[PDB]
Amino acid sequence: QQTLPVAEVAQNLPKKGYSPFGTKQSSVAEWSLARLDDLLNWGRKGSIWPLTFGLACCAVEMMHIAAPRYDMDRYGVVFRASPRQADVIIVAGTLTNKMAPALRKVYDQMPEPRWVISMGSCANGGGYYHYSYSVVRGCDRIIPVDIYVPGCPPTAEALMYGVLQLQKKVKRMKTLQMWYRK
Amino acid sequence: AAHGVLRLVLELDGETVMRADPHIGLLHRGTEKLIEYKTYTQALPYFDRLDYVSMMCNEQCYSLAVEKLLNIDVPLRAKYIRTLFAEITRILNHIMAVGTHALDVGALTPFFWLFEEREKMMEFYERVSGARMHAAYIRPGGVSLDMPLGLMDDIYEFASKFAERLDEVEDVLTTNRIWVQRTEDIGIVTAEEALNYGFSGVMLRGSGIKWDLRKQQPYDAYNLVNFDVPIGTKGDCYDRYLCRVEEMRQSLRIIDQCLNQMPAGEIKTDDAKVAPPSRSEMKTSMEALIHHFKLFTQGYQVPPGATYTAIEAPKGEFGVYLISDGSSRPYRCKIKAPGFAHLAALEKIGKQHMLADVVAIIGTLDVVFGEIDR
Amino acid sequence: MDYDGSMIPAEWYGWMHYKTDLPPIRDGCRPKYKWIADHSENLSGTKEAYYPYSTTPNKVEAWEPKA
Amino acid sequence: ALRRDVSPLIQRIRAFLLGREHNLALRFEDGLADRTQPQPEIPDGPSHLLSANYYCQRDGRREVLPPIDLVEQQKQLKLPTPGKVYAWD
Amino acid sequence: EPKDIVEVPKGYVYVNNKELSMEFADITDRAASTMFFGELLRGFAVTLAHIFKEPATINYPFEKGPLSPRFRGEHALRRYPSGEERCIACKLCEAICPAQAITIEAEERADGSRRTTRYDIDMTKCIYCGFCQEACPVDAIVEGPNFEFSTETHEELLYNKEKLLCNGDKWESEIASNLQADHLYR
Amino acid sequence: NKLSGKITVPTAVNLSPISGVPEEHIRERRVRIHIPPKNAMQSGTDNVNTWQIEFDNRERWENPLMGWASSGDPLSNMNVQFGSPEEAITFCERNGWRWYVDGAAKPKKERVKNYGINFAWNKRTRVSTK
Amino acid sequence: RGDIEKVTHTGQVFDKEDYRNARFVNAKRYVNENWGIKLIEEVPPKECTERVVFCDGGDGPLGHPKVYINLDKPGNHICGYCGLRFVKK
Amino acid sequence: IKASTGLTGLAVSTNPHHTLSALYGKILRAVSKMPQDASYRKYTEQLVKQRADSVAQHKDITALEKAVGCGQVEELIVQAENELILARKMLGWKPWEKLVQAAPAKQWDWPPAQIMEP
Amino acid sequence: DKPTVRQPDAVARSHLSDFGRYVAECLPKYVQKVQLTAGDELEVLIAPEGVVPVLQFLKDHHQAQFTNLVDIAGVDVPCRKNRFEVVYNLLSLRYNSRIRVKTYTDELTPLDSACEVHKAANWYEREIWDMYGVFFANHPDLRRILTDYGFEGHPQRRDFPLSGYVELRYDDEKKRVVCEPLELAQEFRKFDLSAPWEQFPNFRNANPP
Amino acid sequence: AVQQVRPILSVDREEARKRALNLYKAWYRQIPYIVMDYDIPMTVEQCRDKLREEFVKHRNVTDIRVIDMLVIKGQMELKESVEIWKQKGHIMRYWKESQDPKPTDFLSKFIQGV
Ligand code: SF4
Ligand code: SF4
Ligand code: SF4
Ligand SMILES: [Zn+2]
């Protein structure tokens, strides 16, 4: 476990930079590829489009986030209905066996780079129905989950905090910079 | 507009929907079996999950079932708090139904304006119970816990402003021609056909039947509140929508009566063998600790028997048929959610209407999910 | 620009949520014990991340041939 | 000087457009309760009465009986109607 | 007002009994409404107006809240004012936990005290119901107020006693505040 | 020549196929009809008045990750109650299981349990203390 | 790294050749720095006059249930709940 | 005349007395075929005759409504028609006979699964 | 003078009690027993054959006029030779009262259908068929409702493991979701919550054979 | 040991076969459509072969009533495959291709654990 620095330590330290990669690149190609990754991540970070799967009980919070108290399009997030145009999927609610193939199908019909947020306990690990004959214990067993938002349901603040955490993950992803090594 | 759950297998000719087979059961979470394996106290949140749009009304149904089995009564202050939050949930549910319905038809602005005010009400649930939704605040011996001071006043201003908010959307949307023609004369539900299909709630009350559980089989402090339910005479989605709107208004005056007359006193049934003791008494006296110990580990034996109960939940007559074998563990807990019968009738209601009509019909059914399959 | 939701410390958290109306500068009635740690962010996706592990020393002892 | 409001002009047009006298909706600290409050005391109950308070003579769970058989009830011993007729009409 | 169409007794309000008049002023009113969309104009001007209301978006994460002292969030295992663990392994929290998300194994520390060895919570099975803390006889475990505990990996959610103790240390001040607020009231 | 289509069929109708239990469990698992044991350090005996059936333990290992008690055996917790062993055997057959009853106990033989024997002139049974 | 070397107060270190060490190649092994055994040891044993004292450990309803501890024995007497220590002499 | 029945589908019906009278006659004959020792018979006559005797004194439909109670004429005729179907089915059912089946022992006993003293 | 203990509606007990005898003596061949549960509701215990006649009698006759059929609640009770019990909980708006009809059946013999009586029941019979396997005769379409397709066994029975026999996952070899034998991360830990001390004497010898 | 009890559908063992074989007709006739409709690996011959074995799954059913129910299940599953309510996963379920046939001879069991 680590802890935040103290006031004087902050005073010594410089600006934390903007691109999470930093600005230590050696050669022209390195420095150039650093910027292009930064632009790409900036695009994919600023504009992110959930699919609004929202099966149950959790869905109500998935709507309150769209509501005008913790506005989410403020951050550049919009609910596109069509999975071909949706970039992110907030799986929320329980995943019953009847639904499992449906979720799988919806997921891979969506084009990548696709990130999944598992909202609520029901999706995270099956939640409160974990020992049930009809529920997928978690949603990790159908799809690759990216961010877990604990809660039952998570308070709207918690959900969109997780969204920002996804934005941070979208910010630090290294595709061009490290293709250069590939 | 399909609640994320519903899956209608439709067979269409042109654009009209001929055969409409709904496959309820895309959510069913084996909750009857789980309820059996756990204890009455443990089993309580299950009901709050069911019909998740109605938070407290679901719990009140279960708590009344147990109180009828245990042969117990709650003090007046507990009754009034239950009544208060029963109606606050009523306003919550009807906002949810109206807002979802407005999106079904395709109007965004109403949904957003109301979901502003939904935030204030949820904050109130958060103030009392500590959870946005899914409180556990209603329990068999009365409410779990007392109310924080000043929550009365905050409720007053919220009720004060709600007339303005509701009227803004009401004037915007009730009269609007598109909405009127989009909903009116959709899925006529005749009186006799309504009864024989097992309807209830504002659906029934809209079709013309003067029935209601609050006025006829009163179960809570409603004995001490005067008010009138709304009724329609056209059986349309439109006049049904109007009935919901007037219900919001009528509930508001119900909060007026109750919040004005709230008496002091205890907040829990006096039987420490039924409801848990307070912590202060627990940490000092002995059998308070034993009762704290045994209630939380084993629960309380409920005398053997079967009992049914129903409540005027916003969707309709939500009911729980509970059978106790005498142990501390419920033997069988069947749950009758109004959306069940309300949706079965769709296969007949939706005959020959246009596709857009079908979606709007699903909205006016207001079949929230979880309560249908579980 | 790496602001985060968890940067708020404990003593200020309540005030920041309208959870306590008493600024920490004003109410010194809160505990001032020693063991209290210092704040930390949601250390996730990094080498500093927590990861769970068994907290019970092993159950059954194996017979040792040497002894 | 009390609540952040748009400038008086826009207020007047806003009232005009709505057609009803407008009252503010955002919640201010002044508007809502004293947000830190004194400690509440919950008054003691009527069964916490200190004497003549036997559990045996006030308990319900030990009071309930099994279901009775009505025919056999009669064997121990205005067309009847389930209840007051309701004009559900 | 036009007369009704069905006579109503009390305890009810018919929402359509009002008659649509056939008086010439009444028909021409409706006709003019349709010919020039007066009703749409009313709704149109409403939304124009309602631009001039200030939006209620909290500038999260800078601005944020509000919650209440009872909010049920991150779990934490508290410690006495001396620093000693409050939990005594009475195991009620597990016995009540509706989701069965708690697992406990306790023994005697060398001092001879009744204390836990493993104390585990799965916040992918917990429902944040708070039955655990309402049951614990020494306030050992509490639904701390943190709610931004979001993880990229599922394994990171299964807390053990070490993680739970750390949260208790981290959040002790705030939890102390709430309990002082609610103990006499809960 | 009928009573609403009544038919004559044997009383013992095996229902294994219709049941839905996998044949693996049916063919590798037994049932242990018995009466639940009386707890040693209790004295009330109104939870051992019923005849109970359950299935033999299969296995339990520990999850490598977190050291839980993993178990990939479904009928481990399964437990049902009956009023009399013959009822249970009837049920157990109808569901096509293998079982073997476990005779509970013979009727308790009356014990005199007199108070006076505590104080006797000749018999050894004089109590040493009170 | 020391994180995967420390002895949890419960008394666990992954053996030096144990594959369950692998899980920490990229994540820290949290181990708490306050060990209740050491702390309560530091707290001195309070003393009284009366044969029988009472502890709640904490304060009011913020501690453990009130418990009465007799001190007639020569040695210390440890509170069952909080581990506080008493000595009458 | 009342404008509406207050219910969808349930339309205002004229000549209610004629319809009610005709319905009462048929049901009386329908029970006429029944055996003379059937409780269903014994009561239906007195109930129906009470209704069919109240039908006359109140020419006004509203007056008749108050006198008969039990709801408005529009539904009331439907009540009568239902019972017509009941009698025709009742004659076909022969429910006045004695018990078809005796419940097995311990069928309707609650709680279940408890040993007993013989 | 016991505010904790509620006091039922006595006059309601009066009406339901006399009415219950009315039903018993009007349907002798079917009504096996009529009892008044202490919760003021009225139960009507019939033999399996009279299901429709009782329901048809109730919905139609003046004095019953029990039109709405709230639900078909299914109960399972092993140790009853024909165990599967059914409950038809009805309402009467005309008189503002509730009534319950109950019947039994085994896992094999079929059962009468209420589809021809109340259109409301149609889905319920489908639900019990899915959840217990109680066949219904003359039911129009007995398709399963809740359980997923190709589900074997009826889970609400009490001889069925809580977690079921199989569970699903996703295959990459096959780009598809496959059902597998059960495998639980943490076996569901029951708790044996049995009372050693009889807490209820009144039900002890009452209701004996 | 006989009981005088209600029927379900079939009154005699031959009517039972008549119903049972009717189902076999629908399933045999359906197979080609499912091969087309459901994009799954299985081919007509294999589907036909499985249909044979899956009736052989219970050859020694004896009671008239039990065999009636087995047919009732089949008529249901027929319709669920006839119409395409099912999914490619659901239909393939009959093969159980996720798990390798577990060891059966004593040593393989012994060497691979209980
Ligand atoms: S995790 Fe909680 S909020 Fe989400 S669906 Fe499950 S019960 Fe509802
Ligand atoms: S209830 Fe409290 S003291 Fe008891 S085991 Fe749980 S955390 Fe420890
Ligand atoms: S909050 Fe509820 S579900 Fe979560 S650990 Fe506590 S008791 Fe269990
Ligand atoms: Zn102490």
Image (cartoon, coloured by chain):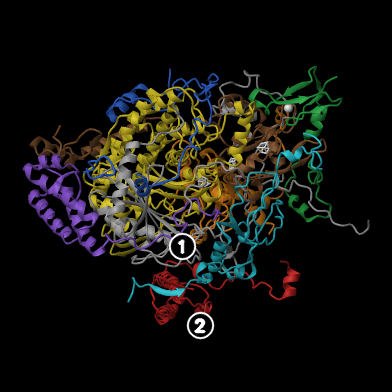
Chain colours: A orange, B yellow, D blue, E brown, F cyan, G green, H purple, J red
Which of the 4 image quarters holds residue E17? top left
Nearer-the-camera pick, B219 or I42: I42
The secondary structure type at the circle numbered 2 is helix
Q: Residues within 10 Å of mark 2 (few under 14, many from 20)?
A: few
Q: Mark 1 vs ligand 1: CB under 8 Å?
A: no
For mark 2, name the chain: J
Q: Position of residue H28 (x, y in %)?
A: 14, 56
User: Which disc, if any, is residue F96?
Assistant: none
Quadrant of the rendering where the C terminus of chain G is positioned: top right
Nearer-the-camera pick, E151 or B205: B205
Q: How many marks?
A: 2
Q: Circle 1 is placed at which residue position?
A: I82
Q: Circle 2 is placed at which residue position?
A: J45
What amino acid does circle 2 point to? Glu
Nearer-the-camera pick, I197 or B362: I197
Q: Does F107 appear above or below C35?
A: below
The secondary structure type at the circle numbered 1 is loop
In the rendered structure, the answer to whether residue E179 lies left or right of residue B307 reads right
Q: Mark 2 vs ligand 1: CB under 8 Å?
A: no
For mark 1, name the chain: I
Q: Position of residue E81 (x, y in %)?
A: 72, 26
Question: Furthest-right residue in view?
Answer: C67
Q: Does E98 appear above or below E141?
A: below
